[PDB]
Each structure stands twice: as C-alpha cells, then as structure tokens.
Image: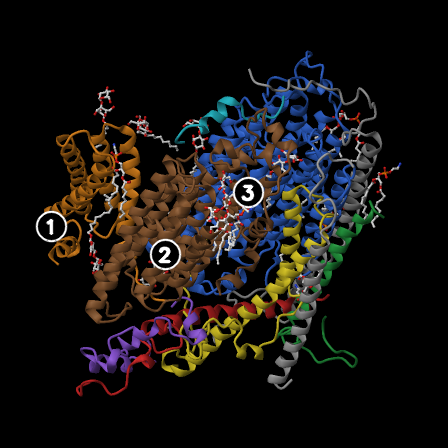
Chain colours: B brown, D red, E yellow, F orange, G purple, H green, I cyan, J blue
Amino acid sequence: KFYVREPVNAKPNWLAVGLSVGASVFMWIYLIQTHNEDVLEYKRRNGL
Amino acid sequence: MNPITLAIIYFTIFLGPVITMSSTNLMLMWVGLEFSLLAIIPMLINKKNPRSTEAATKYFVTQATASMIILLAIVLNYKQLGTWMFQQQTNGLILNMTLMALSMKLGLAPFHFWLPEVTQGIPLHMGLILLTWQKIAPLSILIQIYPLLNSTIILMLAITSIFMGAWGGLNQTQMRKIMAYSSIAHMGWMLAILPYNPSLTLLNLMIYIILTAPMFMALMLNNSMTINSISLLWNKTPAMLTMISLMLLSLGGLPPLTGFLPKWIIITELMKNNCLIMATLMAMMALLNLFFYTRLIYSTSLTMFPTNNNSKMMTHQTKTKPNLMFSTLAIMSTMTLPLAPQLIT
Amino acid sequence: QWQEDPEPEDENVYAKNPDFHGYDSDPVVDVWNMRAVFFFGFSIVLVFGTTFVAYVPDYRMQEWARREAERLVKYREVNGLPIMESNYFDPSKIQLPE
Amino acid sequence: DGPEKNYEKTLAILQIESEKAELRLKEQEVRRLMRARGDGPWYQFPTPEKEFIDHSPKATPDN
Amino acid sequence: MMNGRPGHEPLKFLPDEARSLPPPKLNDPRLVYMGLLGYCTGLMDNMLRMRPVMRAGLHRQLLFVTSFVFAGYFYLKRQNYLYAVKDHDMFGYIKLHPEDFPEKEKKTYAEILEPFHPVR
Amino acid sequence: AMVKRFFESYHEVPDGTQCHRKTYITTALGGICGIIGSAYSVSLNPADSTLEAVARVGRYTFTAAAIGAMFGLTTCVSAQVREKPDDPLNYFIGGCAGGLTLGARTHSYGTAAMGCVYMGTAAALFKIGKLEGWELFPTPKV
Amino acid sequence: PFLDIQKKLGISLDRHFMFLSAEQPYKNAARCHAFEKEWIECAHGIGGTRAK
Amino acid sequence: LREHWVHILVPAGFVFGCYLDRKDDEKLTAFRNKSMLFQRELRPNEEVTWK
Amino acid sequence: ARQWQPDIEWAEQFSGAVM
Amino acid sequence: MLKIILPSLMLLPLTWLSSPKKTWTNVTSYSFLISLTSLTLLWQTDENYKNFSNMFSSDPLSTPLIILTAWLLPLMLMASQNHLKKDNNVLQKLYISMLISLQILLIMTFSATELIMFYILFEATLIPTLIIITRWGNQTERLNAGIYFLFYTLIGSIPLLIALILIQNHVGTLNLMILSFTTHTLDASWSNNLLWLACMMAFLIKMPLYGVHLWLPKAHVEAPIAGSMILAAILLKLGSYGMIRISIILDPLTKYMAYPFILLSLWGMIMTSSICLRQTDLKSLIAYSSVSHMALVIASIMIQTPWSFMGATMLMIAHGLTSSLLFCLANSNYERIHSRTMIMARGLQMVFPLMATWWLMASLANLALPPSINLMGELFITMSLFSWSNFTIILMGINIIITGMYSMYMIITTQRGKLTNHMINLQPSHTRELTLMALHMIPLILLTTSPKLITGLTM
Ligand SMILES: CCCCCCCCCCCCO[C@@H]1O[C@H](CO)[C@@H](O[C@H]2O[C@H](CO)[C@@H](O)[C@H](O)[C@H]2O)[C@H](O)[C@H]1O
Ligand SMILES: CCCCCCCCCCCCO[C@@H]1O[C@H](CO)[C@@H](O[C@H]2O[C@H](CO)[C@@H](O)[C@H](O)[C@H]2O)[C@H](O)[C@H]1O
Ligand SMILES: CCCCCCCCCCCCO[C@@H]1O[C@H](CO)[C@@H](O[C@H]2O[C@H](CO)[C@@H](O)[C@H](O)[C@H]2O)[C@H](O)[C@H]1O
Ligand SMILES: CCCCCCCCCCCCO[C@@H]1O[C@H](CO)[C@@H](O[C@H]2O[C@H](CO)[C@@H](O)[C@H](O)[C@H]2O)[C@H](O)[C@H]1O
Ligand SMILES: CCCCCCCCCCCCO[C@@H]1O[C@H](CO)[C@@H](O[C@H]2O[C@H](CO)[C@@H](O)[C@H](O)[C@H]2O)[C@H](O)[C@H]1O
Ligand SMILES: CCCCCCCCCCCCO[C@@H]1O[C@H](CO)[C@@H](O[C@H]2O[C@H](CO)[C@@H](O)[C@H](O)[C@H]2O)[C@H](O)[C@H]1O
Ligand SMILES: CCCCCCCCCCCCO[C@@H]1O[C@H](CO)[C@@H](O[C@H]2O[C@H](CO)[C@@H](O)[C@H](O)[C@H]2O)[C@H](O)[C@H]1O
Ligand SMILES: CCCCCCCCCCCCO[C@@H]1O[C@H](CO)[C@@H](O[C@H]2O[C@H](CO)[C@@H](O)[C@H](O)[C@H]2O)[C@H](O)[C@H]1O
C-alpha cells in the first residue's frame, strides 16, 4: 500500500455506482417515454 | 441528546410550520407558531454556556410576547365576526397589531434588535435553521391576508429593515451578525412587495434561503465566526473561495447572478403600482449591502491574510465535508439568472 | 518579527536563454509562442482582414447612392425639373390643421 | 445573402417586438381592472366554505 | 394573482388540461442549460472534496446531469401551463368586457402635427 | 381626526402666503420628529440620571423644532420675495436653511454642509412630488 | 390555507368549525345562525372583493 | 490525440454558432417575400426568396 | 517589487468587536 | 452574433483543458481567429442595420466597438504574459478566464437590442474587472481602487435601472428599434428632468464626466496591465455607447438639460489636461489624458449633431487604440524598474531606440497629428462645437495647446536627456513587447486610410 491509514474510498462503492447509474438510465428512459406520450397526446387533442 | 429526543424535537420543529401552513383556522395557525417556538429552544441552548442561555432567553421572551399579541388579534376578531379567520370586514386595528407582532417574530426592524444577538449566541447550524426555516411560518400567515394589510405600515417596516440591515451589517466583524443583518435586509424586500404581489415574496424568500443555506454550510466547514477566521480559507479550504465569492456577490444582488433577480423584479412590480419613492430608496440602500459583502470578499478570495504555523497540520488531514447539497445550492443560487422567466411565473 | 519569505531578486531573462523572445521560460515553447502571434496576428488577421475589408462592396450604399444621384441629376436636368425640391413630402398628402 | 433577408427578418423581428409591447400594456390594464373589481378570474379572495354550514333541524325552531 | 381562479385544483403539479399544450423539446435551450448546471455541480463537488475535477466520479456527474434535465423538463412543462393560463384568462377577460378595452383608430402622420425641435 | 387636519392646513393656500401659519406647522412637525427621536434615544442609549434624560429630550426637540421653523419660514419667505410659488428652488433654499440651523445647533461646519445639501435636495423632491403627484405609500393597483 | 393539503386529501382537520353556523353538538344552533348562514351563502363563489 | 484534441473546441464553436444563426433565420420568416419593398413573383424553380 | 499582501497591522483592523 | 459569441465561449474550456505549456499559445492563437470572424460584421452593403435575432443586432456604432473588443483580447493576453510567469498554473488559467469573460460580456453588451439586456451585461463587467484590479493589482491601494470603481458605477447605475423600468412600464418594451420609431416628445415637467438625469448619470459616470472621475485615476494607477488596457479602451466607451443609444428617447430635454454637462466637459477637460503637466506618475499622466479626451466625447454627444456624433465615434475608436498603446509602453518600463515615477528613468532612447520610436508614434497619435483618426475626431468635434457656439473655440484652443505640452513632455522626459546609467537592469526589449506595440499601431494606421469604417450612425 501507499497510505498508512487506508482510504475510505479505497475501492468503488459498487452499490452506489450501480444505483447511481441505474437511476440515470431509468430517468432518461422514463423522460423519453414521457415525451413521446406527450407529443402523441398533444397531437391527438388538437387534430394534428 | 439521545435519538429519541432528536426525533421528537426535530419532528416538532418541522411540524410547526406545516401546521401553520396547512391550517384554515387561525388558532391552529397560532398553535403551529407555538410548536416552533417551544421546540427550537432546546436546540438553541444545547451547548449550555452563558451565551447560548442568554440567547435562548432573549428569544423566548421576544417570541412569547409576540405570540400573545397575535393571539389577541385572533380573539378580538372572533369577538367582532364570530369566525376564526380574517375577513375583508376585520377591523383595521386588528390587522395592524397582527402585522407588528409577526414582524416582531420575523425580526423586521424596528422590532429587530433581538435577531443579531440571538444569532450570535447559538451554533452555526441553528443559526441556519433560525434564519431560514423559522421564517416560513410567520410569512405564510402574512401571505394569506395580503389583500387586507395596510401598505403604509408594511412599507415603513420594509424601508426601516433595509436601512437598519445595511447600517447594522456595515459595522460587524462577527459572521453570525453579518448573517442576521443580511436576513433583516432581505426580509425588508420580501415584506415591501407583500401587499402587491405575494408571489414575489416567495421568490425572494426561496432565493434567499438557497443563498443563506450554503453560506452557513461554508462557515460550518471550518467553524469560522469572524472575518479573521474566514480569512484563513485560502490556507484551509481554498477550493471554497470560488463559490463563497459568487454567493456573496449573489447575496448582494449584483448582476448577472440569481440574487439580482429578486431585487430587480420587486422593483419592477413596485413601480407597476407607482411606488417610485420607496423603490428608489430601497435600491439605493441595497448598495450598502454590497459594500460589506465586498469587504468580506476582499478578506477571503481577493487577498491572502497572514496565516499561522499550526494550520500546516490542518492541511495534512482529510475532510469529509461539504456534502452534495452545498454544491447543488451554490450553483443554483448564482448561475440561474438565465432561467428568470421560469422562476417569476 | 513574522515568518515571511525575502523578496525575490532581479533576474536577467537573457542570462540563460540569449534568444529569449519574451513569452516563456522554456526555449521551445517560447519560439512557438512567438511564431503563433506573428502568424495569426500579422499573416492572417492583418493581411486577410485588411483584404476582406477592402473588397466589401458598396459599403453602406456609398457607391449606389452616387450612381443613383447621377441618374437623378441627369433625368431632372433634361426634363426641366428642379435639381432638388424644397419640400420633401408632397404638399398634397399633408392635411394641415385649420 | 441579399438585402432582402436582412430587411424582411428585421420586419419579422419588429412585428414580434411590437406585438409583445402591446400585450404587456394590455396585461397592466387587465390586472388593474380584475384587482379593483373582483369580477374576473384573478384576484379572487377566499370566502368561508359554505359546505360546512349545518342544515339539519335544530334543537330550537328559530334558525 | 391566479390562486383562486375557477377549477383550480389544490397542490396539483400539472393539471390535466396542460396536456393540450406542446411539450418542451428535449434539447430545449432551457433544458440544455440545466444539463450544464448539473455538470458544473459535479465539477464543483469534486473541487470541494479535492478530487480530479473531470476524471473523478463520472457516475455522480452523469446523475447530476440527468437529475437537473429530468427535473427541469417537468418544471418547464408546468411554467408553460401557467403561462398559457395567464394568456387564456387575460384574453377571455378582454372579450367579456369589450367596453373597457376599446379599439382605437390611430391617425396617420399626415394628420398629426408633431412639434419640431430644431437642433442648432 | 383633527391632528391630521392641522397638517393639511399647510397646502390649502399657495406657497408664500399665510406665512406664519405655515411656519407654525413645520415647527410643530419638526418637534414631533424630535420627540420621536428622543424616545428612541433615551430608551436605547439611556442617560446616567433622570434630569439628564429630560435634558436630552429637550435638546433634541428644540433642535428639531428649530430646523422645522427655519425651513417653513425660509421656504415661505423665498417663495414670495421671488413671487414664484410652484417652484422647487424655494424648498431647496428652505431645506438648506434648515440644514444650516442643524449645523449651527450642533457645533459642526461639516453637518451644515451635508445638512444644507442633503436636506435641501430632500425638500426639493418633496415639492416636485406634490406638483407631479407622487405618492409615498401607494395602494395596490395591480 | 397556504398549502391546501386538507382540501387535496379531502379530509377536514379544522375546516368544519370555522364559523358560528357550523355544526354544533346536539344540534344546538349558535346565536345569529340564521344571519351568518345567509351571509356565507351570499358571498359564496363571487370572491372577497365582490362580496364586500 | 490526448493533448491535441482541444483544437476542435473553438472550431466546433464556430460551426455550432453558424448553425445557431441559421435557426434564428428560420424562425423569422414571417415576412419572407411580403415586404412592400422586395416582394416579387416566384421564379420557375424558386421556392423561397431567401433561406 | 512584489505584490503587496496584507500584513499583521492590516488584519488587526478586523480583530475588534466592531468594524 | 452567435458565431462570434459561441466560439468565444469556447476559449474558456480551451483555457482549462489545455496543457500547462500550451495555454498561452493556444488561447492567444484562437483569440486572433475570433477577431477575424468579427470582421464579417463589416459586410454592410446597405443602409439597413444587421438584425440577427430578437437578442443581438449590429449597427455602424456597435460594429467598430465590437471589433475593437475582439481584437483587444489577444493583445491583453500577450500583455499579461510576462508579469504572470511566476504564478502557478491555476492562477494563470484563472486570469485568462477573467479576461475572456470580459470579452464575451463586452461583445454581448454592444450587440444587445434591448436596454434591459444592455444594463445587465453593462453591470456584469464589474465582476471580472473588480477581480482583476484587486486580485492581481500590485500596491496596497488596489483595495481602495476596487471600491471606488465598484460604487461609483453602482450608485449611478441604480437610477438608470429605475428609469429603464419606468420606460417599459409606459412604452411596453425596451427594444431599441421600437423606441426609435415610436418615440414621443417629452414634456418639460420637473419629473422628466429627473428621468433625464436618471437615464444619463449612469453613463456620465462611466465616461467619466469631470467631477465624478476620481475612480478612473485610482483604478488605472493600480490595475495590472490588462486591467488598464480594457478600462481605457472599452469600458469607458460603455458610457459613450449608452448615451448615444438612449438619448433618442430623451428629446427635447437635451437642448437645455445638457448645459451643465457641456460646461463640465469643456471646462473639465482643461483642468484634466493641465494636471498632466504636473503629474509625477507616468501611469497617472495617461489616465488623466483619458479623462480629458472623453470630455470632448461627452460634449459632442450632448449636442446631437451629425458632425459631433461622427467625431465622437472616431475619437472613441482612436482613443481606444491610443490609450492602450500608452499603457502598454508605460508598463514596459515598469516591468524593468518596478517604479511608476516618470522622472526616475530618463534618456531611454539611448538603449531602446526602437521602443523609443513607438513612444514617439503613440505620443503623436495622442496629440492628434494629422491625418491620424485622433485628429479627425478632435477636428469634427471642434467643428460641431463651433456651430453650437463660437466661444467654445477658446477652450478647445487652450486644451489643444496643453495637449501638445504634456504629450511631448512625456516623451522628452523619459526618452531623452542623459541616460539614468545606474539602471543596469534595462534588458533589451522583448519580441513580445514590440509585437504588442505593432499590433496597436498598425490598425490605427490602417483605419486612417479607410476612415469610412468608424463614422458611426450619422455618417
Ligand atoms: C434520529 C432519528 C432517527 C431515529 C428515530 C427514532 C427511533 C430511534 C431508535 C433507536 C433508539 C435508541 O434509543 C435508546 O434510547 C434510550 C432511552 O430511550 C437510551 O437509554 C437511556 O435510558 C436507559 C433506560 O434504561 C438507560 O440505559 C440510560 O439512562 C440511557 O441509556 C438508549 O441508550 C438508546 O439506545
Ligand atoms: C420529518 C423530520 C425532519 C427532520 C429534519 C432533520 C434536519 C437535519 C438536522 C441535521 C442536524 C445535525 O446537524 C448538527 O451538525 C452539527 C455540525 O454541524 C453538530 O454540531 C456540532 O457543533 C460543534 C462542531 O460542529 C461541536 O462542537 C458540537 O458538539 C456539535 O453539536 C450537531 O450535533 C448536529 O446536530
Ligand atoms: C462574471 C465572471 C465570472 C466571475 C467568476 C468568479 C471567479 C472567482 C473569483 C474569486 C476568486 C477565486 O479565488 C481564487 O481561488 C483560487 C483557487 O480557488 C486561489 O488559487 C490559488 O490559491 C490556492 C491556495 O491558496 C491554490 O489552490 C491555487 O492553485 C492557487 O493558484 C486564488 O488565490 C483565489 O484568488
Ligand atoms: C447666511 C449664511 C450664514 C452662514 C452661517 C450659518 C452656518 C453656521 C454654521 C456654524 C457651524 C458650527 O459653528 C461653529 O461651531 C464651532 C465648533 O467647532 C464652535 O466654535 C467654537 O468651539 C470650537 C470647538 O468646537 C472651537 O474650536 C472654536 O474655536 C470656537 O469658536 C462655534 O459654535 C462655531 O464656531
Ligand atoms: C468643483 C469642485 C467643487 C469643490 C467645492 C469646494 C467647496 C467647499 C465648501 C465646503 C465648506 C464647508 O466646509 C466644511 O468644513 C468642515 C470643517 O470642519 C469640513 O468638515 C469637517 O469638520 C466638521 C466640523 O464642522 C466635522 O464634522 C469633521 O471633522 C469634518 O467633516 C466639511 O467637510 C466642509 O464642508
Ligand atoms: C426639513 C426637510 C424635510 C423635507 C420635507 C418638507 C416637509 C414640509 C411639508 C409639510 C407637509 C405636511 O404634510 C402633510 O401631510 C399630509 C398627511 O395627510 C398630506 O396629506 C396627503 O396625504 C393623505 C394621505 O394620508 C391624503 O389623504 C390627503 O388627501 C393628502 O393631502 C399633505 O399633503 C401634506 O402636506
Ligand atoms: C454623483 C454620484 C457619484 C457618487 C459617488 C459615490 C461613491 C462612493 C464611494 C464609496 C467610497 C468608500 O470609501 C471608503 O472610505 C474611504 C474613502 O476615503 C477609504 O479609506 C481611505 O481613506 C480614509 C480616510 O477617510 C482612511 O481612513 C483609509 O485608511 C483609506 O484607505 C476606504 O478605503 C473606502 O472603502
Ligand atoms: C436619486 C434617484 C433619482 C430617481 C430617479 C427616478 C427617475 C425619475 C422618474 C420620473 C419621475 C416619476 O415619474 C412619474 O411617472 C408616473 C408614472 O410612471 C406619473 O405619475 C403619476 O402616474 C399616474 C399617471 O401616469 C398617476 O395615476 C399617479 O398618481 C402619479 O404617480 C408621472 O409621469 C411622474 O410622476
């Protein structure tokens, strides 16, 4: 090792990494699905 | 204090404003004001030394006296109208006594002399709570009766608060007083626009909260109460200088920072109502805020004050602060002017 | 007294590098910084920027307006009209207060 | 491009900026009337909810 | 101002009639600036903690960008509805009180006498 | 209420006329500011006695009365020697005489200069306010 | 209220005893129940400024 | 390409800026070929007077 | 010369109770 | 303008993401290529101004100023490069960032189409500029110069914000084209007199007008070199650009409200010029030279005649290049002897014969030698001021005489006489220092051959 006192962030917190990435993927997929469901709803309610 | 006490006390602190904010009846609004007053007291006096005891005492007798006056308004109104809410027909003097009492609870000048001292005797995190979360309950009452408030009382209080907050803060070397007088001045802006557009009072409150929160968090990082204590930041947490400076300019209302938006929109809406004279003095005395905010910036980021030998040990060590909230509130409180149209309405 | 560095001394920039250009302490970074300023500063901006400005045509209609004034000063002289009228707007179209 | 584009864009801009200017003046006139007269959708101030009036027969007749 | 208008549901974030309005474009200049405000936060976070500003913690940086665009998208949708309602109420008021917003005939400059101010 | 009527007697008649009635009003008006100032003064920065307390009240109220009497006279005297009623320069001359009186009573040449300028401008803007109908505390229109 | 939570959740924490003409125990009318019940029904829906 | 990539930063900005101005034009075509001064009839294969 | 940076005398003016 | 702005916004990532040994080369290379792109604005073949969108638009007044700003960024980088060589890397990149930020705001400030947008950008420039003067200034007085600069501006700028809001609450908009085509004559009531001062004092302070100018000699005398270059060349011209833009909506009150300010400028310029005769500090002598030139610019704008505007626009660009050249030259000595006293170093032509040539040419531009555009401005301002009234020639005659004395006295003192031979640290002029002077002087000579480009709006 290098540090006498082992760092708290010695290795990635894989729980947080997967959770951190998981939320991001979910939010983009939810955001994009929501957008399409709005453009369809928007068009449908207005005769386009 | 043990976890049971914190859960009970912190829940009650949170509970108070939620009761005041969700309540139709005035007595339940008063009840929420009591919950906040009672539960904050143990938090303020936790360190138990001569100064926090005086702070918790001055706070209690001020806020209890103001509570009794508010209750008198709620009761004289029930005598006059047989109802537990203020009406268009509520006596004029009943409304004014409510205003003065609530301003006494907010710290608005000339009922302000308690606030800088109480903020001085308590720890930084309870100053954060006292100068932020504790203002929502009295303000939420005021926003519910803005059609009724006498504007002459409101503008004299706001003009006074902007002047006294500027003059008071100009003489302070203690950071906690600089934050109290900062609060007094901003409450002047929230209150000045209250009878005209209560939505702008909420914008000015929210922008003030997200500026005042990280500023306290920044002082809580090294526990720095003085101008000389905060001057050592270049040799302690130099990564913090970039955002302390902007937040201080942002608190000062300087463009193109988010803190210009509240003053600018309040001035704009005041002059939609022909409130020219008051608006001009308000903006002209807000300049004094920027001077003693600038003086702080001079001492911290734009110069390097002398440092001491023992600070070298401080650098060998590793800090686990600040948290992810400081960065989020720092950016939003300074770099969000280009989103102004989405904030006003 | 307090702990403080002494004031740093008066260095000669040419002592170690006699071809010092003024930009950098490292000779190789130094020459390429001089070269960049001369190329983008003089060969590109001043030369092409000056050329591009000399061939902007009819700048602000300074040229069209002359070509048009000659057309009008001819047309009006042969047809006996005045070279330039006193009134700009026709008096017919102007309803004055009574 | 030719002068057309800059000219007709400037016409397009001037129209946008002009329509906005009239809407802003029209909103002040509207807000002045709704607030002072309470006959519009804005500045409606609360009056007690009548759904909580007790309509039952009472202990006494005169009510 | 608009607190007590008719049909105003309490604490409803995006009422149903907002769905008749076109959604914010995903790459809206306003949403994109949210993405950059998120990215800076991740950079400021690394700076405050003494980490490599751009290399460190990309999972955090990705989630700061995603969080601000996600929230900004829905917040933008609400402000569009609030702004749409403002015009809706403003114009329907003009219609219901025509005598208060009279159409005016503006004279042409042929008929107007603007005073002349010499600059000598 | 009467006490409001009295202070509106100041603008029933064009400036420069009924000169003593106006001088009396602004003398009372200055006294009211002096009394309000003393009340805060004695309460927040209390004196060492009680006679010394009352002395400070008298010293502030006569000084405040003196400023008001010199303002309301110099304004009305200038406004009729020049025969120019609707004129802010009258109130600038009166406001400065008020400022000069303040410095005279305070043993401070510096105050007289600051007082002559700051109060003269404040007095002029009060006149320009009444001509153009600016309100200090307007009521909500929009 | 400032956060019409009670109205949103459809509950009534304190909304049901706001005024005299509210429900009383054992159906005992309050003094001036008739008049108040009239005033609250008159000023219902027209807003505060019109009602004044 | 791990110390010279920075040279697409500014050239990209110019290209992105030029494209952003081409949109501002697309948004302001409400008076294209309608001015009292330049309005004319469209030539055979002419769809718009300017783009 | 060298950039002036605050000395002990300069900083002692923020060391009081008031400014 | 988004093709001049977006690439400029990219010099900030490029500053930070570049190597330590490439920051100064890379940024200064791309700054030149950005000032080339700004020449596209000069493609004005018609009498209609360029309107790019609802935000930005360029006029014959805002184009010379826009270009002068973009060209000045590469100049200031080279000026700041030798006195920052001892700073660690993040300080250099933080200095480069503050200079770029000042170029981005300045370009947006001159291209803005609405007064409120102008005001915010016109106030944002205080931040990078306050940081520059204070963080990187040299003497203890830099702290008092930042306050004087910050609060002269802000005190003047609060009334302007009020007045701009009143204009919109009444007209409905702040668009500069609409306010031009719908302007209504103002009444001569006592309220509009104050509206006039409200709209003007902000810009009259930034010029600065005589009387309220003590911030400028304080700011200059303590700013780093690039602080003085931007101040003397662009930030003073924010005042002039504002007054021209907003004075359209202020008629006819400018026919009488201007008298106090024509008189402070005409008399004030003599007071400032005569100061330069007895000024013991070289950087101070130039700063008062700026105050006395802007006096004519104030005086000529207040009379609103086609000639007076034309002379002021030329003098704005001419002063922009000339004052900056002087500050760079005074800095070149200062970066050798670290003293600003003008009489300390003498006879410098003996050891800097080429740098003594630039001194002469800068000095000749300052005293407005024909045919330089410095004279065209002074000459067309005099012509208009003569028509306004014939006795202004008395005061302009004097100021022209004094302007010759302190210009040559500046050259005779420092470049002639015997050498101050104890100054063994007079190193030969750097190639960088000489390029910096050629870049100031060549454009100034080129603009004399094509004066059409800086005639402004009226001509
Ligand atoms: C902070 C909010 C989140 C927590 C939410 C609330 C639930 C908390 C659950 C954890 C509870 C632990 O809280 C528990 O409190 C008790 C008293 O009640 C403390 O116990 C205390 O009283 C006991 C009584 O016999 C004695 O031993 C002694 O006086 C003291 O230790 C425990 O030391 C602590 O373990
Ligand atoms: C619905 C319920 C809502 C619950 C809301 C909860 C809000 C969050 C409250 C956070 C409180 C913790 O925040 C507070 O942190 C500070 C440090 O800054 C600690 O405070 C500390 O101050 C100094 C140094 O910092 C120490 O000498 C001291 O002994 C210690 O108390 C407190 O012990 C802790 O209480
Ligand atoms: C509108 C334009 C944008 C304005 C942006 C505002 C930028 C911030 C201005 C305030 C100054 C920031 O403050 C600046 O902090 C940096 C690092 O953070 C310090 O930097 C210097 O000191 C610290 C330690 O002391 C080192 O980590 C650093 O490498 C060194 O260069 C500067 O000494 C200080 O001046
Ligand atoms: C028509 C215009 C008339 C202009 C005059 C009206 C304005 C007068 C302003 C007087 C200002 C103060 O007046 C001046 O105060 C000083 C205070 O130094 C006092 O002066 C006296 O005491 C001071 C101590 O303070 C001594 O130093 C001084 O030598 C002595 O004369 C006097 O009271 C008066 O000399
Ligand atoms: C175009 C430039 C115009 C320059 C104008 C010059 C005219 C100056 C006239 C000022 C005359 C009054 O002179 C006045 O003298 C006093 C001397 O006590 C100065 O004031 C000084 O003394 C006073 C006492 O009176 C104290 O409050 C204090 O120590 C200080 O202010 C004032 O600042 C100055 O205003
Ligand atoms: C020494 C410098 C001080 C500068 C100021 C100079 C003050 C001298 C002028 C004395 C003014 C008397 O103040 C007097 O106040 C009353 C209070 O109702 C004003 O009264 C006015 O406002 C009230 C609002 O309450 C209206 O209802 C009323 O119709 C209107 O007259 C008078 O218009 C004003 O004349
Ligand atoms: C017409 C509109 C124009 C209005 C312009 C108003 C601008 C206001 C500028 C505020 C100046 C504040 O000035 C502040 O106090 C003084 C001014 O001398 C300076 O202080 C300086 O001089 C004082 C003497 O009084 C010394 O005590 C101090 O050691 C020295 O630094 C401060 O360093 C500066 O911070
Ligand atoms: C030291 C700072 C100086 C502050 C400078 C601020 C700029 C000055 C602005 C001009 C003065 C106020 O200008 C004011 O405009 C308002 C409306 O806007 C009008 O004033 C009037 O407005 C409307 C009618 O329009 C009336 O119903 C109202 O009672 C009255 O206030 C007058 O036009 C003028 O009284």
**Is any atom of residue F128 visible in this view?**
no
- Expressed as whole percent of the image width and height from the top left, the position of residue J371 reads 66, 39
Query: Up-down: is J318 above or below F129?
Result: above
Marks 2 and 3 on same chain? yes
Question: Does the CB distance between marks 2 and 3 fall below 8 Å?
Answer: no
Label 2 sits on residue: B35
Label 1: chain letter? F
Residue closer to the observer: F44 or C71: F44
Between marks 2 and 3, how big is the CA–CA gap? 34 Å
Disc 3 marks a residue whose amino acid type is: Ile
Looking at the image, is mark 2 or mark 3 nearer the viewer? 2
Q: Secondary structure at mark 3?
A: helix
Task: Classify residue B317 by image quadrant.
Answer: top right
- In this rendered view, identify the residue nearer to me: F23 or F136: F136
Residue type, label 2: Phe
Chain of the residue that carries numbered disc 2 in the rendered image: B
Whichever of labels 2 and 3 marks the residue nearer the N terminus, that label is 2
* Point 23% across, 63% down: residue: B75
Residue at 57%, 80% (x, y): give it: E20
Q: Nearer the viewer, residue J111 or E41?
A: E41
What is the quadrant of residue A47 in the picture? bottom right
Secondary structure of the residue carrying tag 2 is helix
Q: Residue furthest top?
A: J422
In the image, residue E19 sits, relative to residue J175, either above or below, namely below
Amino acid type, callout 1: Gln
* Residue G44, image x, y percentages: 32, 80
